[PDB]
Amino acid sequence: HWGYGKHNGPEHWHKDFPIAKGERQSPVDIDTHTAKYDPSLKPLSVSYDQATSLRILNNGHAFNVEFDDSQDKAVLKGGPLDGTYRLIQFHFHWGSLDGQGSEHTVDKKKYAAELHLVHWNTKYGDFGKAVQQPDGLAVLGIFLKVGSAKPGLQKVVDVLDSIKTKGKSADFTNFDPRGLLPESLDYWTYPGSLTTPPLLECVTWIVLKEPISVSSEQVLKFRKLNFNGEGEPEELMVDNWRPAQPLKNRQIKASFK
Ligand SMILES: [Zn+2]
């Protein structure tokens, strides 16, 4: 099945998921000179004070930090969005080396990693229904550069040993995702897709301009994870990013001047 190797990576996905060659695929390159400022865009409202993290899971493609999404406890609103989007999980994409790892690029620059906070539109009742709708999801994307450590990431880093291989989970309560955000909420936005199969075209992307800094030691720990299950040949979980896809008939809008 699908993955990030030579034989099963992004360049193969279209055979099982023909929407891979669709009109609104993600990620994309953000050309900062052609993204236009849209004064009609609102500030983003990120309301994470009541967020309830539950568990962390290695799904064989990344690790997900999962939230209780059975009530409006952590929500995204405003910005480009109409209505209320509930946080369900976050995860990262990262590289084998610090010079690659992000999915989106900025003027063809690749960051070391990219954080995706995934939210679903409450008007559709559940995640599974939301991903069938063109406005079903809102994903907040945050770039990671290597420099100073991110204190708010360390709790995630230190549990990774317990979820080394595919299918492992661990309790992960009381984690506050506010500690993963940069200072500024200035963003770019465009309509796109999930970046992993099934590649559904259901996402409003909100990509923050300001990266967070993580330390080399933090990223090194991500790269010790495994794609494989327990007692299988070890294949380090690295380079779990899809490259930029054609922009097609889309415009990228900026919230800032
Ligand atoms: Zn992602």
Image (tube, rainbow, N blue to C red):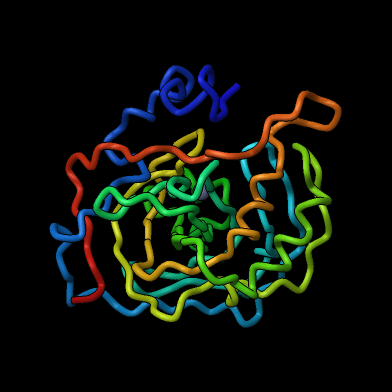
Q: Nearer the viewer, residue 193 or 29?
A: 29
On the question of residue 97 being in view, the answer is: yes
Residue at left 20%, top 60%?
Answer: 32
Q: Quadrant of the C terminus?
A: bottom left
Residue 237 against residue 133 in the figure, above or below: above
Residue 198 against residue 193 in the figure, above or below: above
Q: Nearer the viewer, residue 19 or 26?
A: 26
Give the percent coordinates (x, y) of residue 154.
69, 68
Q: Is residue 248 left or right of residue 180?
A: left
Residue at left 45%, top 28%?
Answer: 10
Q: Quadrant of the N terminus?
A: top right
On the question of residue 140 being in view, the answer is: no
Give the percent coordinates (x, y) of residue 59.
69, 41
Residue at left 37%, top 50%?
Answer: 110
Q: Is residue 169 left or right of residue 82?
A: right
Give the percent coordinates (x, y) of residue 100.
44, 45
Q: Nearer the viewer, residue 76 or 160?
A: 160
Residue 228 against residue 110 in the figure, above or below: above
Residue at left 71%, top 71%?
Answer: 175
Tell me which corner region of the image, top left, top right, bottom left or bottom right, holds residue 152: bottom right
Q: Nearer the viewer, residue 99 or 193?
A: 99
Give the percent coordinates (x, y) of residue 215.
58, 64
